[PDB]
Image (tube, rainbow, N blue to C red; front, side, top):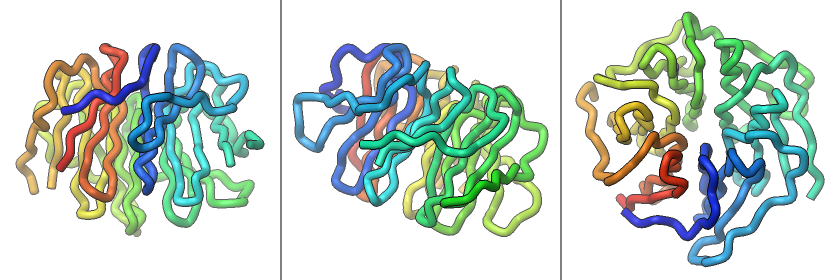
Length: 243
């Protein structure tokens, strides 16, 4: 593993990576989002304003950055105009994901639900998950399958594309799973926050990734080359492992 050269992070939560290898991190305790260009030593604070304990971050292929502004019950995006997305009724939203169509998915953690907003729409859809308990991370693959970490229930669930009912993924021994990412090949990675580890599922037999010294890992992201980035929330750092 290598430790990325961020400085002064305070409980980093979410992480996202784009196709040029730029890494974006929500610096939750400093109310800011920072980024590192590939191979750079200086981080840049993005011109978001008014953030309060931001949690999740996602980036689309057009370089637009979406952040769940947890403490303000809202989702904001940056194209340098910041705009607030027209979600309604959110309660401490935390995970965010965006598909190729520009559809934004949010885990509405305080309301035990997952909602989505189609691009340029004033229509919020509640996804038909059931029995969720503080859902925390969300990922969506190219086929439209949605994965959610059901933090409070120590499980990961998914709604297969076109399905009306969720399935529980065959992970074993999770303790408050927090972040989820899915690569091009359908491999799912989950930060098992309460066990200080990152696991993955290609299969019903999971693997533990060979990170060392994690302390409540939170966010996870994977790039097109299979490199895995994890916010090591308890150690105020971001670490990565190449494939």
